[PDB]
Image 1: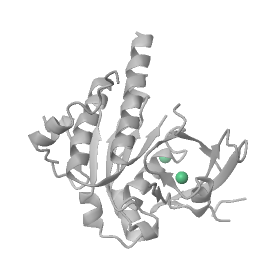
Image 2: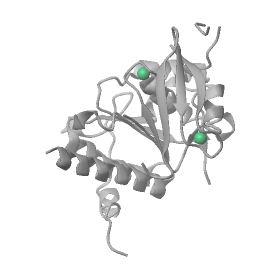
Image 3: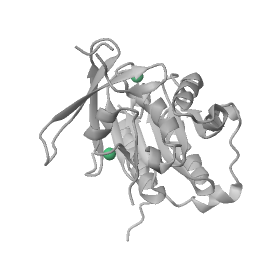
Image 4: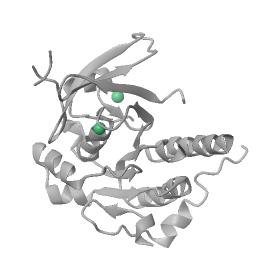
Amino acid sequence: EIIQITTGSKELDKLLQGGIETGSITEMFGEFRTGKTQICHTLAVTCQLPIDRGGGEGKAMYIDTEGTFRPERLLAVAERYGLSGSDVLDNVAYARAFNTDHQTQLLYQASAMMVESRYALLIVDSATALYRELSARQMHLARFLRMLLRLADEFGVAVVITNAHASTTRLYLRKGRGETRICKIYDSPCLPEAEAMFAINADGVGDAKD
Amino acid sequence: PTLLGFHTASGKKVKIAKESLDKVKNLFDEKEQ
Amino acid sequence: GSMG
Ligand SMILES: [Cl-]
Ligand SMILES: [Mg+2]
């Protein structure tokens, strides 16, 4: 059964039919500051929440390639949700991929870790940055993406990557005024296009306010 | 090679049992069915 | 907030 992890924003959660889905990949498009990395940091904490509070009751794994992982942000989100800051940090496993080979190798370690402890989320920010001969890189990336799908299938974790299989949800983020941001989703038998506004704060992703 | 593995956000190295790695050795194979 |  699927678990939907809260993004911290009621509007964004509604757009996502509940939140970030375990068992599949959510691919977010946008540059740093559009909210993609902020969403990742928020999810690394909310995935630890009790299921009734919108969490996945599991640990988070964060593979960074940009050098933008910030433990202090996790502490702020933890305080916001009334969670132990120390426990939250101990429950987020982090690694920085040095190159594309390392990026893929980390998935083997990830799989071993998921056998030992319960994880609810795997973040890869960014899944493509290190890839930017050409055909060789494209095949390697394709393999990497299929491996992520296998992990989601095998362990039932939500896989969120920043930058497709039928189960992949693609989110296109853009800047709004000030701290507000907009997320847009496409081709949906329910609606051709749908959008939701959210905000990035010191303590994570929240709803946009006037 | 601490730089190539995982650490908790609090800076603690994450230990992985050799058996655990062995158990998932074939997880990513795309063998013909 | 900054919402218009
Ligand atoms: Cl961001
Ligand atoms: Mg969802």
